[PDB]
Image (cartoon, rainbow, N blue to C red; front, side):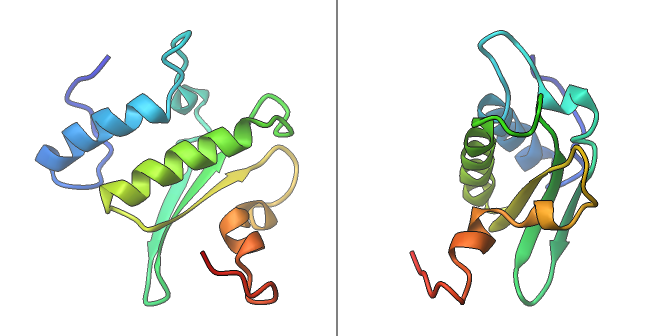
Length: 119
């Protein structure tokens, strides 16, 4: 179900096509569920700086302890980084704690300087 929708980001030409593509990977077209409709995903803040360009996305799941986290992270990060709109993202899972620690994804955790890991 496409249409002239408004994500506000990107020029109307680019946004339409790119979001149409993104919405294919960041949705459940199997049974037809759209996470955005849960109306927590309304909370997204993309902060750009000299350090980098990070898209923060406030999300939640049935119990936030489901292995669906990998799926949303992979599909979201994969597309968003490919769209070029943002390079860094962080999907945080909130159902109890204050928005902060939840925003530490595999990007920050595994590739922390203390680990010295580099891909």
